Image (tube, rainbow, N blue to C red):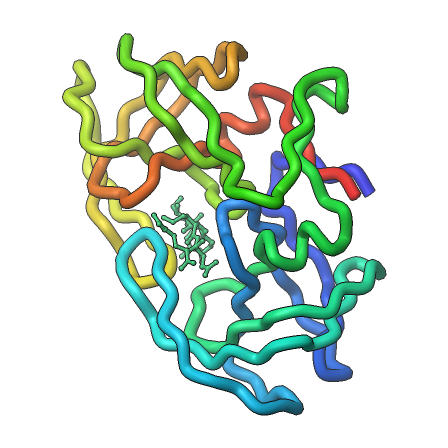
Length: 203
Ligand SMILES: CCCC[C@@H](CN[C@@H](CCCC)C(=O)N[C@@H](CCC(N)=O)C(=O)N[C@@H](CCCNC(N)=[NH2+])C(N)=O)NC(=O)[C@@H](NC(=O)[C@@H](NC(C)=O)[C@@H](C)O)[C@@H](C)CC
């Protein structure tokens, strides 16, 4: 399908013979599902996100059907806030990010989808993250008025400053919207701005 980003790109998956809902997440390296039993041997791993690290169980070579497309690969199981399908399995199902219906650049997911953005007169690198509702930029002395906000992910919550109506050029495409500024480990372009540049998921 072609999936636009006005809503969270939630899809049904089948894993271990059971149905679950999960988020297609281009900002995730790996696939992480809520605590469940999986037929297999596993090993302990730690993974990180916007607010810190959690402990997970790594299962390798697990069959997963993702909106009807087959994958067999690594599934991490643990206390994730949201079930997420990450790049390890998105690449298996042929998923790419596309600008303006496929008239624009296609970005494959073999490596993290990092692009150049311009904000506040400054050029920065940021991750195109379909699993992010909002856009979160590293500490930056943005002018203007703002309101406090807390945003959550793996690890919990960080406190950020919410700025509205900030222009943000992404790979040469003009956008303008809400930008959250705080101690993120990676600059993240989320759905609020991805939609403005006509970004879709396709597989
Ligand atoms: C779990 C909640 C949904 C998925 C998540 C994916 N974001 C990426 C951002 C990149 C890191 C800051 C992420 O955590 N990716 C992880 C997923 C875990 C994984 N293993 O794949 C990742 O790739 N982690 C790498 C490490 C990332 C950084 N590495 C590095 N800088 N070298 C990993 N291998 O551990 N989305 C979010 O974290 C966003 N949260 C949300 O969109 C919503 N919040 C919640 C709680 O649902 C909304 C209601 O606020 C944040 C940005 C705020 C808008």
